[PDB]
Image (cartoon, grey):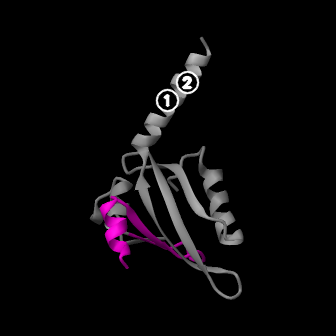
Amino acid sequence: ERFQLAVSGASAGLWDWNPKTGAMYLSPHFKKIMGYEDHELPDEITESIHPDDRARVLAALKAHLEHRDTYDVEYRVRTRSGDFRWIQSRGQALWNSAGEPYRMVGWIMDVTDRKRDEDALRVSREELRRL
């Protein structure tokens, strides 16, 4: 509620997902972060994860939808232009009294540049230890 000031000014994209149907609402900035203009994708879609992250991500979604464990992951997605970016994705599901998810709401942020510099550092450290 004070929320929309939040998800907006961080340059975040909002998402609202139905677990049974697969349907997803996307904010204009979500579409943008995927590399798409507002009109280049509908406000609702019903495959882009990097092959190396796919298992990790799906597993964390399961840990959330089943064990309630926190959902907050970083991973690579293929943008409109087939180029990969890193996003952080965080969200919270809603369950009925039967323990089943009927909704999940969250956001994404583009964290590519931080991930670039972390790996750059990481590689510098490896190489120094090889000397």
Does 44 sit above or below residue 113? below
Q: Provide the residue designation for mark 2.
A: 125
Q: Mark 2 touching mark 1, by CB under 8 A? A: yes
Quadrant for the N terminus, please. Answer: bottom left
Residue 102 to residue 89: above or below = below
Which residue is disc 1 drawn over? 121
Q: Position of residue 12 (x, y in %)?
A: 37, 61
- Residue 83 in view, yes or no: no
Pinpoint residue 56: horizontal percent, then vertical percent: 64, 52
Residue 43 badge: none
Q: Magenta segment, which residues?
A: 1-26
Q: CA distance from mark 2 to mark 1?
A: 6 Å
Q: Examine the image and state in which quarter residue 59 appears.
A: bottom right
Amino acid at the residue labelled 2: Arg
Report if residue 80 is visible in the image.
yes
| Residue 37: % across, % down | 28, 59
Pointer 2 local density, CA inside 10 Å: few below 14, some 14–19, many at least 20: few
Image quadrant occupied by the C terminus: top right
Write the residue at 54% across / 30% down. Answer: 122
